[PDB]
Length: 311
Length: 312
Ligand SMILES: C[C@@H]1O[C@H](O)[C@@H](O)[C@H](O)[C@@H]1O
Ligand SMILES: C[C@@H]1O[C@H](O)[C@@H](O)[C@H](O)[C@@H]1O
Ligand SMILES: C[C@@H]1O[C@H](O)[C@@H](O)[C@H](O)[C@@H]1O
Ligand SMILES: C[C@@H]1O[C@H](O)[C@@H](O)[C@H](O)[C@@H]1O
Image (tube, rainbow over the protein chains, first blue to last red):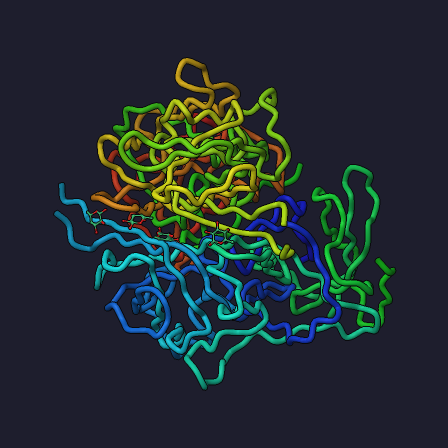
């Protein structure tokens, strides 16, 4: 079965690490952190890895039940919630995944809305509530691999114990010094001092002059100063496509061309690696300034020795 | 002729095309009295997007624009006038042949979400940000997205900035009480109440007796009050994306599809997938379709409109 990519322009793609549209392509060659995100991880022959799942609505989402309000040193009112799989089935900690699929894969204060629809009814319809909430993924109480996490609210009382609870992610609460936003630092999925397991592997350029190419989205902020971004290796639609197709990878590296369909011209070429990430021959950091109607077209299978035309 | 195909996605791998929600169940309601003419999740089988349908899951019931004015409510809350652009940031051209900016909500109700802002201008050199819960009443006379402006209301009384880039992230509904006017099949008046909506995707209905529409149903969160509201779409967003990609020619007015259990390989039921992008089944009851979670629709063959479906 021939390998293919979807024909979706940048303006028709979404981020696989947060529910955002792709805003720009981006490079950062001098990045010192190990790039090992766990969402938006899929091999070219369609094997989902890390915490990656298929739903755009599942990325950085949680489902579960609030248990109780809990004490925390930090500002706000805090709540423990058990978490299930996104499909409602119990999360089995013995499954070979880092955490429930969809779990956030970076350190930070994730801002969103907690909503509840009660199990018990009264015209035999249940009571509901929703409030803004923050999940600090760096907190010692962030233990999704153990089946429970903690969130904080501004609301002090109107969160119900033992009721079905949904977290809808919206952005970040803050990127100030004490908010520990670092998109390449993984949460400790089982808690402080524990080793993460079953991780999707780190990615890096191997060839001289090459750097990773990211699909970048700017992420909203609840408050404060900043213009934070989330970089994914492949957009969610590519994850969905590769998973569907399951085309055998005929080498370790696919040559792809970024094409302008209006002119038919190649703007640049890139290596699409077997494990599901892109590299380009670029010697600068920052956005790739190109029209959003551009898209990657699969050209051919090459190998690690192939030399990319400089961007 | 390029062969017609559907994605192989189970219900648990599909999302709603009319609100950012996972698909929870398949659903029928044969005695529905309303005209079904939703505008999101509309796509012909040969890949033509219709109504206000666009491809991004993040675009469904989303808005982008700038706040222009603060207006206090008489009783409670603050209202904010917002000019809206296309979701890609370009100016919305009201003369374009669409009902409203793509992504605009396609139903009457109080849509609950978060308005966020990231300022354009900066002596620190990082822009200021804010976000607050917000409600958009799509039935309101001030909901005129085809004219390029809407209004949202907040509990927050002051901290929303004018002239700054503004994003609406939908989350659910504010209420489904009587005075919240939730009706998933009542279209907003995109240009205001005395004006006719234009460029609409056509209404959908079964043509043959004994058939009813089959919906992909999602339950939508509530900010408060009692209720278990649901949003039914004609096709999931992944189907829209797939059909748009493939643009396979339609070889008849109807694609026969089978809902299959891959574990047994057995067909659970069959359905007509109509040219205009919707499903009908031979079922004479309302409610969820009880079917295994591993199930998915498989394209069988092109048939004729006169094809008689096996009763469910
Ligand atoms: C619920 C809380 O209401 C307060 O007035 C706000 O200042 C906070 O941002 C938060 O939204
Ligand atoms: C930078 C400041 O952050 C705060 O949280 C906001 O409430 C202000 O409007 C401002 O944007
Ligand atoms: C921002 C407002 O804060 C209040 O305390 C809440 O009761 C309202 O639901 C709303 O969220
Ligand atoms: C029915 C009631 O609606 C209100 O909005 C909520 O604040 C309460 O918790 C309760 O669910």
